[PDB]
Image (cartoon, rainbow over all chains, first blue to last red; front, top):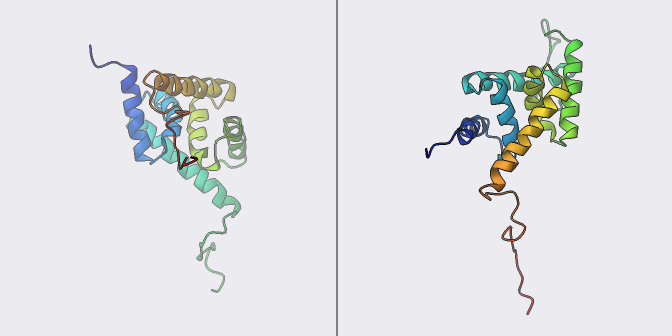
Length: 80
Length: 80
């Protein structure tokens, strides 16, 4: 009787949170994700990443990144 | 992969972001959520909210953070 159920659903989220090093204010999102991923972190963690990769890749598609990329070309190589 | 149609998936993701007024770094989450909610914001917005309520509701029950409105801070107060 001491171990409840809902508290556990949050436990799993606590991991999906510390793993992605997210602040404590993003708990409602780790909650829905696990809610859709059958709460299987091994599955949900595979979604967020596939997500980070999307967002991070999406932008790099429009070349809208003034970071220190440095090496940036295609096909063979311009000349530098 | 599958560009064009992918740009829109970000359009919905954006609303889910501005509506909850989330920073630009939480796009990978608004991405997974819509991915399972058929990307139907009207369907996902129901999860996140029900999510904010869970975390928010789950907290006021133990009075963890939810803003103290008092012992929050102090900095200084040497008036007299």
